[PDB]
Image 1 (cartoon, rainbow, N blue to C red):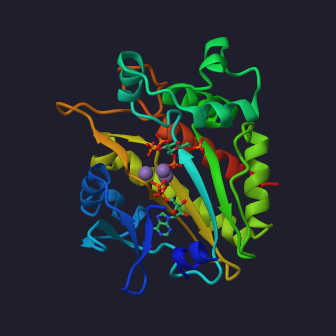
Image 2 (tube, helix red, strand yellow; image 1 turned 120 degrees about the vertical axis):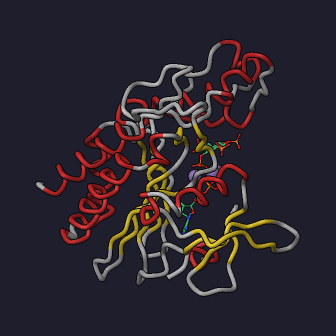
Image 3 (cartoon, rainbow, N blue to C red; image 1 turned 180 degrees about the vertical axis):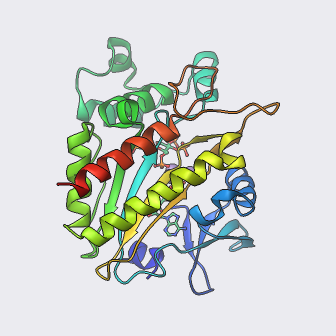
Length: 275
Ligand SMILES: O=P(O)(O)OC[C@@H]1O[C@H](COP(=O)(O)O)[C@@H](OP(=O)(O)O)[C@H](OP(=O)(O)O)[C@H]1O
Ligand SMILES: Nc1ncnc2c1ncn2[C@@H]1O[C@H](COP(=O)(O)OP(=O)(O)O)[C@@H](O)[C@H]1O
Ligand SMILES: [Mn+2]
Ligand SMILES: [Mn+2]
Ligand SMILES: [Mn+2]
């Protein structure tokens, strides 16, 4: 019905207009959504209607992706082998901002993960934290990870930081679709069509797509949709340069592994469909 309905039961605010939602405007994300409305990927992303001012602040006016659904179930998949910009690596070398928050979350999961010096600092750099998160989740090996589920019963979970193996990921999707063969078939048809759109997209070949998600939405009526969201760290390649989006990331090459992730994700859902 609406995301803000769920929020009621961060960067998001209720829109006055029916079927819309407001997201705090960021310069890279605004640039991206404007381009995407004219791209092959137009139908694979939420409609972007422009910017509005609320309480002296700028908001993206977006399609509420939950609007067409009756009690939506939602799963957010973070796409890519890398979840931070290469510029974070330069910043942490020349002028590191030590992060005490990130030390704590790391310590909780693996007490032996932090180095002697990180333990002494009670702090880690952002790229160290984000690379560690990639390796204990499925990000590094499979090129995506499950971040969160919101269920029709009102329940939500973010308990997926150690969801890493192909079979662990399959079991989360298995629980998410609750044996609805029609929802799974529709998800797979939509992911196949998104992959085809990404492989021909002018936007996609010319942009490093970091920190974006695939939002899976379904309901008890067997309606099922998937969209790309979150273009806050999606940046153009300089001087008409392109990515293949499959080859491994090496600092300098700006590769995101986006399609390595999507390939693996389709493979897992195709496997689940045959179980
Ligand atoms: O390991 P988790 O607790 O699941 O998530 C860690 C956070 O991940 C964010 C992205 O992931 P998201 O798009 O929010 O899923 C980071 O944001 P940006 O990349 O937009 O800057 C945020 O960074 P910072 O604002 O510097 O603290 C991290 O602290
Ligand atoms: N257009 C949308 N319609 C409905 N829900 C949305 C929409 N965009 C984002 N969301 C919800 O908000 C969550 C966070 O979105 P995201 O764009 O990643 O924001 P952030 O930049 O704060 O991480 C998603 O996982 C989803 O539940
Ligand atoms: Mn996000
Ligand atoms: Mn965020
Ligand atoms: Mn963002």
